Length: 400
Ligand SMILES: [Cl-]
Image 1 (cartoon, rainbow, N blue to C red):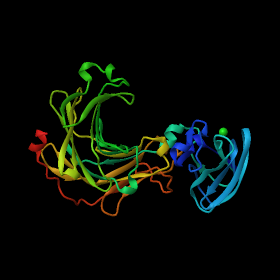
Image 2 (cartoon, protein in one colour):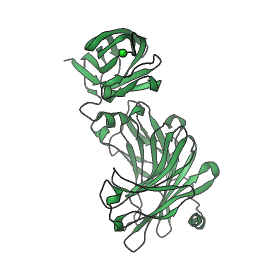
Image 3 (cartoon, helix red, strand yellow):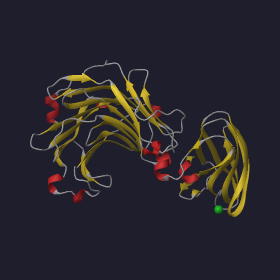
Image 4 (cartoon, rainbow, N blue to C red):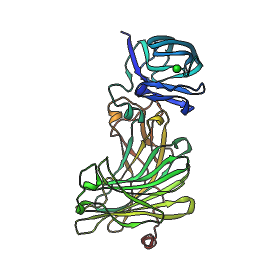
């Protein structure tokens, strides 16, 4: 039987144009002052169906509600929330449904406050953010690729990363060369700032790095030119380093990660970034992790959106030419990548998670942006063992 689908704006709506002219909060749409602003609400339907749309809203205004080219003009004239009819739409196929809101006239300060989109008489199952963190829900599902290492002990992992222009999205972490105890990648942080980040967790489990015993603190061994070193907390704790570097979409950068136990019960982690635009390797940092005796484990990559406001945009990244070097000095081309998604995806509140093969023998990750094809947890992807073995001046790297 058809059912009512109540879609909360706080977990499913975004200001998608003129960001300063409306806001999504725990209340839904508030501070909606600019007629140029567009608010978009997304929910997924499993089968074709009609839907009678209403808004749970209040205000003194005229707004425009749209589903593709079909638009409805809607007056709000109330001080308190009421269920305001919009009109019927026909969803002709499964997938994400995007409903847009735009201000047309405001009798006072703003276009009104919108708490929910209500879709009545809907046939079939739906997915969207409900009974789930709006914050994490809107940030969307992070995705991961894990690469299989050969047998034996790997000391270095090498991976080539390219963020295509279509995948370049502010407030994203493109994590290239992770390992069992931390991360190495690049971020697009603001219009004037992009960072190469390298983080290593302490073995001591705490949310405050100052609560880590001295003999378990991550120690700085080497620091690259212009690199900033500090400590982090609130997601476990440890040491981090970054280099401000204006990386460009469409360019291929190289991440070279060294993990080497010292034989004295510590392991050293040394991160090198190839600044393609300058054609030179940079040292980010070398950190020592105490109470740890490991070679390289769990080489992996991930794609993450930091900003709930950016959830409506996709982001994407390509990873190519994965190599591992054994402690004995032997290079092997890696071929096997396993795709996983985060718990937001597992909750099925966001279905816009994807990864796999490119047509040019790379792997990709893609999330956000409310696209319609997902990929199951644990799906294995493969590449041909082609590509140029890395030619690294090891001595020169040691002088950085
Ligand atoms: Cl108002």
